[PDB]
Image (spheres, coloured by chain):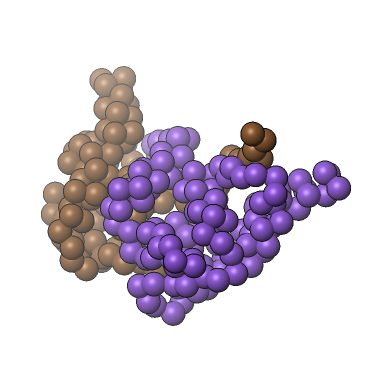
Chain colours: A purple, B brown
Amino acid sequence: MGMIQLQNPSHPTGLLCKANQMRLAGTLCDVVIMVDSQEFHAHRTVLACTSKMFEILFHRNSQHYTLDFLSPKTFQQILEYAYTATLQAKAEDLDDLLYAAEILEIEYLEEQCLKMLETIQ
Amino acid sequence: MGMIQLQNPSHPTGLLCKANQMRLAGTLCDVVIMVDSQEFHAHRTVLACTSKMFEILFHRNSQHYTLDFLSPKTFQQILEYAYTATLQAKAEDLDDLLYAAEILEIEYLEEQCLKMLETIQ
């Protein structure tokens, strides 16, 4: 037969951009991540699609999830990466980020943190 | 100061790919869209980040939302586009897709459906 196809190469990027604007306004946020005192509002789908650990964690439903293997600062860093595809940090945060990245099982961050730590080394 | 930056250009695309695999398995789906008889399980964030109409609709919380301005077939088409960035259809579906696309306010689909209808014309 005959088919028509429309493909928007910007859609993934546009969708994540809007999710990030929703997270900053609190719109449709359905999970709170608790690190030390601080609360981080976010969307389960974005965190579960970024971290295999969160996808596994949310197997057990609750409104709040407490993480204590990392600081609020490291979590914010990874939360921004999940919602924008970029992470910014200080060189002294690399060991903290690698460890969080391995536990959360976010392949890109573990691979890149390792590669940066090793070439410096 | 000194900063380190890691940017994964594949992240948007990887995140949407995983959401699509989650939708097909039913994982973390938190909304059912009802069209004629058929039920479509999906994630609120993906639909609200794709359609300004769904972002507005979900302002009013409920587990189920009924759409009757389009057929199940057209909805499936747009549901696939939302989750993959590609839509496939038959040429005879173009008027149906444009209309659904305008009501749902999915700019890319309205623009492309219009452009295809007009160049054929």
Residue B1 position (above or below residue B26):
above
Residue A56: percent from left, percent from top:
52, 73
Q: Residue furthest right?
A: A121
**In front of the other: A12 or A65:** A65
Residue placed most toward the observer, A104 or B111: A104
Q: Is residue B63 left or right of residue A80?
A: left
In this orientation, does residue B112 appear?
yes
Outermost residue on the bottom side: it is A60
Residue A44, percent from left and from top: 41, 63
The percent position of residue A114, horizontal first and vertical second, equals 76, 53
Q: Position of residue A105 (x, y in %)?
A: 63, 63
Residue B77 visible in this rendered orientation of the protein: no
At 23% from the left and 50% from the top, the residue drawn is B54
Q: Is B3 positioned to the left or the right of A64 in the image? A: right
State left or right for residue B33 relative to residue A64: left
The answer to which quarter of the image holds residue A103 is bottom right
Q: Residue at x 51, y 59 (%)?
A: A72
Choose top left, top right, bottom left or bottom right for residue A33: bottom left
Q: Quadrant of the N terminus of chain A?
A: top left
- Of B28 and A100, nearer the camera is A100
- Whether B96 is drawn above or below B70: the answer is above
**Point 28% across, 39% down: residue:** B106
Relative to residue B98, is residue B20 depicted above or below? Answer: below
- The number of numbered discs placed on residues in the rendered structure image is 0
Name the residue: 20% across, 46% down.
Answer: B53
Residue A77's place in the image compared with A72, above or below, is above
